[PDB]
Amino acid sequence: FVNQHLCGSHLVEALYLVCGERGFFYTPK
Amino acid sequence: GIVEQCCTSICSLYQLENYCN
């Protein structure tokens, strides 16, 4: 699921699945 | 940033993990 173009909700979903209990930051600017 | 690396171009696990806390 990670080795592709990921935009918008699709990118946030990948971050969520990869990072698990760590969480993540989404900084599109 | 992440949009240029993962949306405009092909993402990777390596790069996604740079945005985990």
Image (tube, coloured by chain):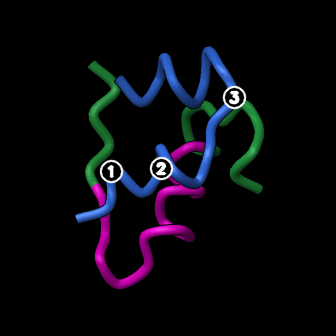
- The residue beneath circle 3 is B10
Q: Colour of chain B?
A: blue
Classify mark 1: helix, strand or loop: loop
Disc 3 is attached to a residue of which chain?
B
Give the quarter of the image for residue A26: top left
Other-residue count near label 1 (Cα within 10 Å), few / some / many at <14 / 14–19 / ≥20: some
Other-residue count near label 3 (Cα within 10 Å), few / some / many at <14 / 14–19 / ≥20: few
- The residue beneath circle 1 is B19
Location of residue A2 with respect to A27 vertically, above or below: below
- The boundaries of the magenta stretch are A11-24
Residue depicted at 35% across the width and 23% down the height: B1
N-terminal-most mark, 3 or 1? 3
Please say if the residues under marks 2 and 1 sit with CB atoms less than 8 Å apart. Answer: yes
Residue depicted at 77% across the width and 37% down the height: A4
Q: Are marks 2 and 1 on the same chain?
A: yes
- The residue beneath circle 2 is B16
Classify mark 2: helix, strand or loop: helix
Residue A4 lies left or right of residue B5; in this view the side is right
Labels in figure, total: 3
Residue depicted at 42% across the width and 57% down the height: B17
The chain letter of the green chain reads: A
Task: Look at the magenta stretch and give its main secondary structure.
Answer: helix
Q: Distance between the residues labelled 3 and 1?
A: 16 Å
Disc 1 is attached to a residue of which chain?
B
Image quadrant holding the C terminus of chain B, namely bottom left
Other-residue count near label 2 (Cα within 10 Å), few / some / many at <14 / 14–19 / ≥20: many
User: Does B3 appear in magenta?
Assistant: no
N-terminal-most mark, 2 or 3? 3
